[PDB]
Length: 129
Ligand SMILES: Cc1cn([C@H]2C[C@H](OP(=O)(O)O)[C@@H](COP(=O)(O)O)O2)c(=O)[nH]c1=O
Image (cartoon, rainbow, N blue to C red; front, top):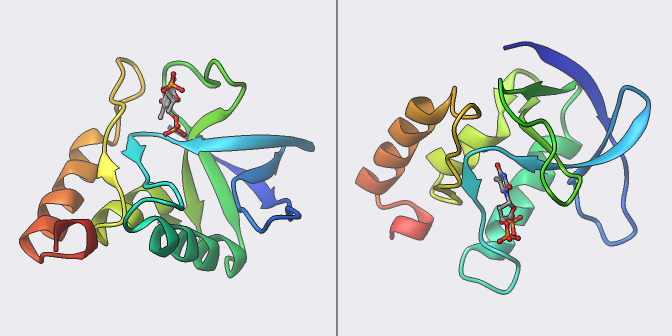
């Protein structure tokens, strides 16, 4: 896999899911995670967590997997990195998302993320508390 550059595009409502990739705006959806929505338990914590990670990054990169690059909603499907640190993994490791949506072809980092979840569960973090 390859990391490619992006930048955060500021949103009116403060969300940090839209990135500028090859010069164009694109909503990205993080591969391999289920992230609680704002109104669910740990929703506000997960949003604050990703927001701090992406907004403070000097460098954002996106990394496509080997399969589909966009979903049925037109969202980019990628591993998102903030100064070399993967957002998808960091959410899971902190118990702020679960490993989920594992489709064929786009599963390169599955075992890496499942290890993070196992560690988060062992430590009773957040969702696992
Ligand atoms: C993570 C991921 C989600 N999706 C689709 C599955 C779900 O479709 P449905 O909308 O029909 O439930 C949806 C979950 O996204 P959200 O968790 O952002 O709601 O996005 C993909 O198609 N591929 C993916 O890799």
